[PDB]
Structure formats: C-alpha cells, structure tokens
Amino acid sequence: SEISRVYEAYPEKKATLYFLVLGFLALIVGSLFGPFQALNYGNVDAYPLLKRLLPFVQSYYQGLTLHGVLNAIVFTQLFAQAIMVYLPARELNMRPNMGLMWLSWWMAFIGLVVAALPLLANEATVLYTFYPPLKGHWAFYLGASVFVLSTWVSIYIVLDLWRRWKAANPGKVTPLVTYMAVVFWLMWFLASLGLVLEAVLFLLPWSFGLVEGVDPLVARTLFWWTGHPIVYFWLLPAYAIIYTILPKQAGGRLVSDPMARLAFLLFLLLSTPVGFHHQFADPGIDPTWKMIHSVLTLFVAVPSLMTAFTVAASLEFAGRLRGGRGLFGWIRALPWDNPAFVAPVLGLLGFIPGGAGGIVNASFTLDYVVHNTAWVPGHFHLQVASLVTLTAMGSLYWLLPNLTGKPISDAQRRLGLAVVWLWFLGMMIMAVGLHWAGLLNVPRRAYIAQVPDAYPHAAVPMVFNVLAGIVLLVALLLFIYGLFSVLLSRERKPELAEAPLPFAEVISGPEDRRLVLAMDRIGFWFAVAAILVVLAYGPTLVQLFGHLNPVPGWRLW
Amino acid sequence: DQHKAHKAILAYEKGWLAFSLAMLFVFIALIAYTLATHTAGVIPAGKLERVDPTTVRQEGPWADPAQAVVQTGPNQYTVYVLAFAFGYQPNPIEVPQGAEIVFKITSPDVIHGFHVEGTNINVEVLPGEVSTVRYTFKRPGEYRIICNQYCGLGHQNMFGTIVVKE
Amino acid sequence: EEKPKGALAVILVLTLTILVFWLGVYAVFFARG
Ligand code: HAS
Ligand code: HEM
Ligand SMILES: CCCCCCCCCO[C@@H]1O[C@H](CO)[C@@H](O)[C@H](O)[C@H]1O
Ligand SMILES: CCCCCCCCCO[C@@H]1O[C@H](CO)[C@@H](O)[C@H](O)[C@H]1O
Ligand SMILES: CCCCCCCCCO[C@@H]1O[C@H](CO)[C@@H](O)[C@H](O)[C@H]1O
Ligand SMILES: CCCCCCCCCO[C@@H]1O[C@H](CO)[C@@H](O)[C@H](O)[C@H]1O
Ligand code: CUA
Ligand SMILES: [Cu+]
C-alpha cells in the first residue's frame, strides 16, 4: 500500500517530487557560495568569514566548483528530468515506467553522492568544466558520468510513453508538451555524445591510472560538443513551462501551437553543431570552422527571437482580456500577485540583455574583446540563473500543490513575491557590475579580492557587485525559510493535488494541420540532426584524433 | 477576434522572422569585414604545432628568456612566450613600436590564458600545442598580461608585462 | 481587436538592446585593434 496513496494512483508524482526536492537542494547548497563570490567581485574578501561558518572549505576556487557543479549541472538536469517527464505523462494521462523511472532518480542520487565527496574533500578543485590537464579524484568523473547517464534512462522513459500513446491512438498527431519533450530528449542524446566520449575514452582511464595523459585540445573539443547544447537542455524545460503553462497562469491562451513547435524543432537542429563559439580563442582549430560555427550559433538565436514574439503576444492577449488598458495597459492587468506568474515574467525581461550578450559572444572576433572576462558570467547569470532558476522557483506555487496537496497560504504567497523580486533585482544589479567590470578587463574565475590594488578602473562596477551580494544574500535566506516552510508545514488539502497542471488552451487556426504534420515528421529531422553534428564536428575531430598528444595531469591546488 | 487574432499574429511571426534574418546577416557581414582587415591577426592559427610540455623549458626556443624575441623580417618579431604556473617568460617582453609581433606561446603544465590589456590579444595556452597570434602595437607603453583561465591557486596573481619601446 | 502592438514594442526594445550591445562591442573591438 501507501496512504498518500497519491503515490499508487499517480505514482509519477512520488518520483517527480524526488527529483525536484533533490534539485532545489543542490541549488540551496550551490548558491551559498554566490554572495561570497559577489562581494569578491566587489573587492571585499568574506572568505575568512565563510571558512568560519563552513570549516571544510579551503579556497575561493573550491567554492567556485561547488557553486558551478551544484548550481549549473546538478540543479538544472534534475529540474529537466522532473518537468520533461511529468508533463508529457500527464498531458497523455499515462504511467511512466516506475521501474526505469525509479532507477534514474537512484543513478542520480548515487552519482551526485560519489561526486560530492571528493569535491567536499578538496580532491577535485577543477571547476564545472574540469579542463585537462588539471586532474581530479577518480570519484568526481565516475560520479559525473553516472549522474549524466541518469538522463539517458529519462530519454528512454519519455520515448517509451511516446511509443505507447501512438499505438493506442493511430492517425493522431503528437500532442504539444509531448512533442516538445520528445525532441528535447532527442537533442540531449545527440548532444551528450561529446561529454560521454570524453569521459569514457579519456577522463575515466586517466583518473584511474589506466593511462598517463590526455590531449587537452581533444578534451576541450568533446566537452564543448556537449557544453553548448547543455545550455539548451537547461533553457527548454523553462520554455516548455512558458509556452504551454504560463499564458494560463496569466489568464490567457497560447497564441500558436505551430510556433511553439517550430521553436523546438529548431533547437533540435542547431543546438549541437555550434561548440566552437566556446573555442574562438583556441589554437589548432581552423579559422574557417569557427566562422561556420559562428554563422550556425547566430542561427540558433532565431528560435528564441521567435519565442520572444509568441510569448509577448500571449501575455498581451491575456492582458487585453483582463480589461488591459492602452499600449501598456496590458502589462498592469496581468496577475502581478502570483509568484507562479511573476517569476518567469521577470526572468523573460532579464533575458533581453542576456540574449543580446550572447549575440556579441557568438560573433567570432568580437569574442576576443570579452572572452574569459567577467562579461561571460555577467551574460549567463541573466540566462541560467535568472530565467531558468526563476522559472523553477515560481513553479513551486503550482507544481508543489499538484504533487503533495499542500496548499500555498497567503503569508507564503507574499514570501514568494519578496524572493522573486529580490532575486530578480539582485540578478540585474550583478549583471551591470560584471558586464562593465569585464569591459574593463577583469578576468573571470578569479579571487580578485586578494589583489585589491589590481583593477582600480573597476571601482564603481565593484560597488554594484557588493550591493548585489547583500541583496542576493537576503533573497537566498528568505528562499530557504520558505522553501522549507512550504514543505515542512503540517497541512495537506489535496483536491488541489490531482487537479491537472494548468495547461493552456491554444488559439487554433487554418494554417495549422499541414505544418504541424511536417514538424511531426520526427525520425526525418532527428536524422538531419545527426547529419548536421556529423558535418560540423567531423573534419576537425578526424584531424585531431590522429595527432593525439597526451600530457601529464597536474594538481595545482 | 480570437481567430482573427490568429490570422494577423501568424503574419507578424513572418515579418519579425524576415527582419531578424536580415539583421543577423548584416552582422555576418560586419564580422566578414573584420577577417579581411589587419585586426583578424589576433585569430589563432589553424596548424597543429605539436610540442612536448615536459621538455619545453630545457630545449627548443622556449628554454632561454634571452632568446625569446627573434627578428623574423625587416619589420617582424617572433616572441617565444612561456605561460606557466604563475607567470610569464620572459618578463618583460620588449618589442619595438610599429612592428608586426608574432606571439608563439605554449605552457609546461596546465592551460593558461594570455590576454593583453588594451588589445584583442586573447588566447588559450594548452600544454603540448603552440598558440600563434599576431599584432602591431600602434603606441608605446607598458601592457599588462592577465591570465584569464583558472589554473590553480596562483591564478589571481598571474600577470605579465609587455614593454613596447618608443 | 487588431494589432498586437504591445508585443511589437517588446520586440522593439529587444532589437535596440541587441544593437546597442553589438555596436558598442564592435566599436570597442576596433579601438583595441
Ligand atoms: C541557460 C542558459 C544560457 C542560454 C539560454 C544562453 C544563450 C546564448 N548564449 Fe550563452 N554564450 C554564448 C552565446 C549565446 C547565444 C548566442 C545564446 C542564444 O541562445 C541567445 C538567444 C536569445 C535571445 C535572442 C533573447 C530573446 C528574448 C526573449 C525570449 C525575452 C523576451 C521577453 C518577453 C517576452 C517578456 C515580455 C513581457 C512583459 C511583461 C513586457 C557564447 C558565444 O557564442 C559563449 C562563450 C563566450 C565565451 O567567451 O565563453 C557563451 C557562454 C555561456 C556560458 C559559459 C560557459 C563557460 O562556463 O565557459 C554559460 C553558462 C551560458 C549560458 C547560456 N547562454 N552562456
Ligand atoms: C544565489 C545568487 C548568486 C550569486 C550572488 C552568484 C554570483 C556569482 C558570481 C559573482 C560568479 C563569478 C565568479 C567567478 O567567475 O570567479 C558566479 C559564477 C557562476 N554562477 Fe553564480 N551566482 C548566484 C546564483 C547562481 C545560480 C542560481 C546559478 C545556476 C543555476 C549560477 C551559475 C553559475 C555558474 C555556472 C558560474 C561560473 C562557474 C565557473 O566559472 O566555473 N549562479 N556566480
Ligand atoms: C530482458 C532484459 C531487460 C532488462 C529488464 C529491465 C528492468 C530493469 C529492472 O528495473 C526494475 O523494474 C521494476 C518493474 O517496473 C521496478 O519495480 C524496479 O524497482 C526497477 O528497478
Ligand atoms: C517596478 C520596478 C520597481 C521594483 C519594486 C517592485 C515591487 C512591487 C511589486 O509588488 C506588487 O505590487 C502589485 C500592486 O501593483 C500587487 O498586485 C502585487 O501583489 C505586488 O507583488
Ligand atoms: C525613478 C524612476 C524613473 C526613471 C525610469 C528608469 C527606470 C530604469 C529601469 O530600467 C532598468 O535598467 C537596467 C539597466 O540599468 C536594465 O538592466 C533593467 O532590465 C531595467 O529594469
Ligand atoms: C552594461 C554595460 C555598462 C557599460 C559601462 C561603460 C563601458 C565602457 C568600457 O570602457 C573601456 O575601457 C578600456 C580601458 O580600460 C578601453 O580599452 C576601452 O577603450 C573602453 O571602451
Ligand atoms: Cu595561468 Cu590563471
Ligand atoms: Cu554556447
């Protein structure tokens, strides 16, 4: 049995609640180093104070890795494994294989665990990119690998549910959330080949003793094969939620099924073959192959410019529907008192300058201005740590009710808003200080507080970084006392908790059908996806795999 | 109106995607422009120049600071720069103003960055491989080299100097 | 009604941000060239 028998009529809720809690937990621990790293870019050293509070910590850079791995690899994937399974299954009112599903959660819990231990014990201070020849404990890569392998099971699970709904429903076109999740999970498989080879072919043998060195150019070239589209593996859960759930929270409709679909098909073609935008300033990669990846990255921006218009129009329509006044009337009609709505909307706003920073980054030679400065963390804090995270945070207010039958009180709803607004206002202020600090040449990944006299042109943007450490300290603390207050409360009123995910009606139309029919030609495009990866990474990897020049690992911490 | 809404909106979708492709290609254009000018000099070279990082400060042109700058044309210098756990050989790099400078950089240990304040010199240094960029300093002074790739605990302290002679 | 003009002023701000950033960074690139 089971008395929240909740978890034996809809057991999928039991597993999704697990991922989620685990995801947000990594995110509380990871983010704790945040404000510490912020006051540092503000040129205050709070680390002796930290190392008090947390004696295990040996350096700024151990911080940086935990922050990185915990926030950007572990928090985001576990959030994708939640959303991208649970939504498909519910829109298709169907059971994900609770055998394969329960497996993945445990592949991840073992994985995370095995990795955390060397990290916590200063044996793997190589940062979230772990660039050879810096060398970490075998435990880190073994962990990482098995954690990243949790998604492959997830892949199958969604594909499973896809295959079964079709047979039971032949002739019927693939329904929206499901189609999304289907190409998403497909992208992530194709994309994950890079990291997977780099571990198996190199990182695993090396850190075990099986071999002596790794070729650093190949290592970094496999890494960034995965390393770009992994950002789209973080973005699209939020996008899925934003396309098909948020116009409903707004009181509106998705203005277009095709557009939502066309967006996601595009992320399937262009997410993977773009990795050299990360390598513009590497040696041994042909300039001609940088330009093509340059062009190709600029095309990956396109599904996202589209998104901007579709979503903006969906929020506008809803606005109007709530007596949405004049040219800007509609903005003030939206539900500004629902953290479910506020979070992803505030994140969309920060996503305006962030996407603009990407475009510069993408443009080959312009990257020489900003590469490896503070600008880069400036940009992606607006992308991953505002949009994606805000979408995860503000979705505590629908998903958690729907999974546990805890209602949100009204004191909690108001806490939600103070976080979300503080989180946003703190993200924006940090964006300015780091964009500017980086345009002044301040390196990323650096304990700069230890060289207080070193970047004096950066004085005022350093005032902006201090100012945001304090603002984001308060936000994080108010988020803990509330994440746990939404959970550890002793209420459960679950009519609320079966009660379907506020999926969104779609304004239908004529020009649908034959277009939705083409995009649903799935096996065709999945293969085009592979042909495009193959041409993009093919000539270069062939070159480098016959000039392997492995070098000794070092530990420099 | 909720289906008339659709008919419009999906035409805008078309016009915004057209405008977007246009603006995007103008960007492709103005990048293109840069690769044809001298400024394209900062782009690392294609060719895989293999070296052995364990032997590099013993034998070859990276073994002797005195021999780093080596005249390679009437107005050309090759500089052998070593980026290592926790500074730069040689230090300073003295180079004449007006001249094409060809930086040949490598590392004996872990990856470094070699980024030159006030220039678009901005390159990753990998153990076992030579990073080859070119530049002409249009005015004299000291230029600080910042290491902008994490490499260990001396990271925040890895700086160098280039003196470009009057 | 008619025109989704709220959404146009959105994509308008987006276009401008995109141009201030790309033009600003282009100018810096040249000035360091
Ligand atoms: C979750 C995460 C991330 C997303 C999404 C993301 C998007 C882009 N990025 Fe980026 N990025 C780069 C280029 C791009 C481009 C072209 C895009 C595109 O995908 C961006 C397209 C986006 C847009 C065109 C924005 C559309 C706007 C929308 C959708 C909002 C509209 C608002 C509305 C609708 C609200 C209206 C409502 C009202 C109520 C008014 C490049 C270079 O080409 C580098 C390497 C540079 C270097 O030196 O390392 C890079 C580096 C990073 C790194 C560092 C990797 C490392 O650690 O070394 C991370 C983590 C990251 C994250 C992310 N990035 N990025
Ligand atoms: C809680 C508030 C946060 C603050 C105050 C903060 C602050 C910072 C700062 C100032 C840096 C740059 C430090 C350096 O490059 O040496 C940084 C790096 C980073 N942040 Fe955060 N951050 C926060 C939340 C997040 C979140 C929620 C995520 C992702 C989900 C995130 C992802 C990252 C990543 C991936 C890096 C760089 C890792 C690396 O370079 O190896 N941050 N953070
Ligand atoms: C013919 C060989 C193919 C291998 C068989 C794959 C099943 C792997 C075992 O998974 C298990 O499945 C159960 C049933 O759902 C769950 O109850 C259980 O907890 C889960 O761990
Ligand atoms: C505008 C940028 C300035 C930053 C500070 C903004 C915080 C104010 C947002 O509070 C909101 O006010 C609404 C009343 O209008 C209420 O409906 C809603 O419950 C409440 O959350
Ligand atoms: C006293 C109020 C009257 C002045 C009106 C100006 C309000 C400025 C709000 O714009 C903000 O500017 C930031 C950059 O500075 C952006 O990054 C951010 O997205 C945006 O929120
Ligand atoms: C969100 C962005 C806010 C931007 C703040 C102003 C950006 C101006 C950058 O100044 C730069 O200073 C360098 C000297 O150190 C010079 O190399 C360069 O000529 C110059 O452009
Ligand atoms: Cu060498 Cu940082
Ligand atoms: Cu990328």
Image: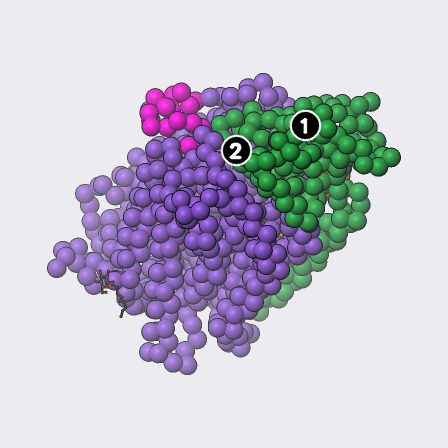
Chain colours: A purple, B green, C orange
SS for dot 1: loop
Q: Position of residue A353 (x, y in %)?
A: 58, 43
Look at mark 1 in the image and give the residue it sits on. B64
User: Does residue A433 sit above or below A111 in this rendering?
Assistant: above
**Mark toward the start of the polypeptide (2 vs 1):** 1
Q: Residues within 10 Å of mark 2 (few under 14, many from 20)?
A: many
Along the line of sight, which residue is nearer the eye, A447 or A351?
A: A447
User: Does residue A485 sit above or below A57 in this rendering?
Assistant: below
Which portion, as a residue range, is magenta?
Answer: A46-68
SS for dot 2: loop
Residue sitting at x 42%, y 27%: A59
User: Does residue B12 sit above or below A421 in this rendering?
Assistant: below
Q: Position of residue A341 (x, y in %)?
A: 42, 49
Whether residue A245 is visible here, answered yes or no, is: yes
Label 2 resides on the chain identified as B
Along the line of sight, which residue is nearer the eye, A298 or A175?
A: A298
Label 1 resides on the chain identified as B
Residue sitting at x 29%, y 62%: A100
Pair 2/1: label in front: 1
Amino acid found under the numbered disc labelled 2: Cys
Q: Quadrant of residue A53?
A: top left
Based on the picture, tell me whether residue A414 belongs to the magenta stretch. no
Give yes or no for contact between labels 2 and 1 (Cβ–Cβ under 8 Å): no
* Marks 2/1: CA–CA distance: 23 Å
Amino acid found under the numbered disc labelled 1: Asp
Can you say which quadrant of the picture contains the C terminus of chain A?
Answer: top left
Q: Residue furthest front?
A: B59
Tell me the tag on residue B151.
2
Q: Position of residue A475 (x, y in %)?
A: 40, 34
Q: Position of residue B67 (x, y in %)?
A: 73, 28
Residue sitting at x 29%, y 68%: A94
In the image, the residue with mark 2 has its CB under 8 Å from the nearest atom of ligand 7? yes
